[PDB]
Amino acid sequence: PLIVPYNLPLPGGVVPRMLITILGTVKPNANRIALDFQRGNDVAFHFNPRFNENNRRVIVCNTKLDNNWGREERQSVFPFESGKPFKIQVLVEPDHFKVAVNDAHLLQYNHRVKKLNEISKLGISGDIDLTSASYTMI
Ligand SMILES: Cc1ccc(S[C@@H]2O[C@H](CO)[C@H](O)[C@H](n3cc(-c4ccc(F)c(C)c4)nn3)[C@H]2O)cc1
Ligand SMILES: [Cl-]
Image (cartoon, rainbow, N blue to C red; front, side, top):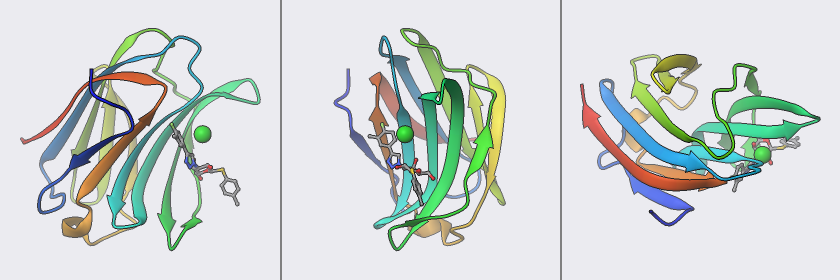
């Protein structure tokens, strides 16, 4: 398995039609996972499954600019499961990141950070065994 937290460079930044695929297995009794598409110190797109936020499972998405988190976007569809293998696919579209988990569409996140070419790394962290992290053009 790859060492978590893992940094996946995205050479030249992201572009529409770029597909990022992450395979891993959630740890037993997981608490949290995060994907962080980063523009330097800023987080263009934070995708954060929370397994126990006041006894609810929720995905929180947000952007961090100059160390400040913005408005959260929340999704109660929660496709992750402690102990089980998952696939996350993040497709960059012109106006949003489009996320599918286990081949089912989950959410879209409109681009707040609009310099897509400057979003040139992806951090993967939290309560997973990480099998692979890669990208391709579709
Ligand atoms: C005013 C204010 C008060 C409280 C908060 S809470 C904050 O909410 C953000 C989304 O709005 C992020 O989720 C933040 N966050 C989560 C993680 C994280 C996730 C998974 C992981 F596996 C690792 C290693 C780290 N890192 N930062 C989280 O602290 C926010 C604003
Ligand atoms: Cl969290």
